[PDB]
Image (cartoon, rainbow over all chains, first blue to last red; front, top):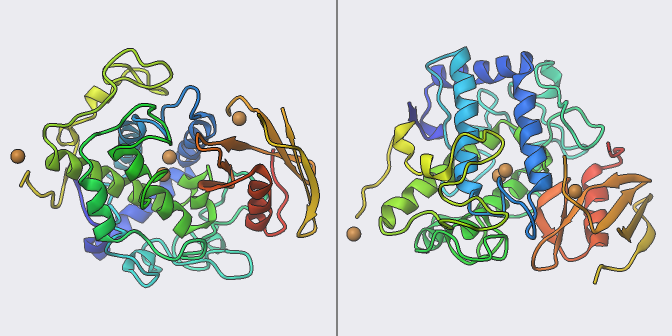
Length: 277
Length: 77
Ligand SMILES: [Cu+2]
Ligand SMILES: [Cu+2]
Ligand SMILES: [Cu+2]
Ligand SMILES: [Cu+2]
């Protein structure tokens, strides 16, 4: 129940994480997470119903989605938890994240195909099945479409924003959620998807296992924000059309509300999370 | 006010746009006659399902970005 910085995992932990992910893929369970994510990102819209993205529920929705995925991992190997990728620190293609013993590296220049690591198409263990085009191999172009990952100074600027979210509760909003998501401002979460490239830059982005480590760090930044702003909390708090209010339930689960997910410690802790200082 | 329609050959591929498990749809884009899901953001920029986190100003720009991303690959509906 401890989520650790990817950079700190032991060789044993990397091995067990990779094996659990590959078993979810083999059994068919992994691809249904890719499919769920794609349905939500293709339906969430700024002027209509929005639940997984571009809306205040972006953070609790992804928190529950990652919990569903972690529990599936733990059904294969109970010792495995989701690691997180602090892209403000591990910001180059030579980070151990991208080593052949963990997620493998960037794609070759001809077709973006990842050529090493456990998820390379040549292994036979990572077919891309849920897809928007014919290609069936994992692709990446690290640093190709945008030069730089966010820096710690940029992250700190967003963490200082006190309001959780603001009307109109979409990609035009001021406030923490939309600056963390990245549709306005210096851009944190969206820019990382663009920097990885390949399927990570598309609606079917959970096809790349780095998806989970990216969102585990976004989820940690929500926890850091809460510690910085103990006086701020999820909004809206009732009666907002098309948006998940605090005590409303969320699709697809229907049985959990943002209110049930604000406190991560009910489900996991981090290796390090600074106290309200 | 939807954008205008367009039709051109971009990097060898036909891209078309027109006003009209996924969202509603006020505008349609096609790459070689296969529909490309695209979506408009509140500020008037566009994304597509092959470049979802990267707003571009117009539906033609999203079609071109998709052709760039596909590297010759057929789109799947
Ligand atoms: Cu998402
Ligand atoms: Cu994301
Ligand atoms: Cu205080
Ligand atoms: Cu749609």
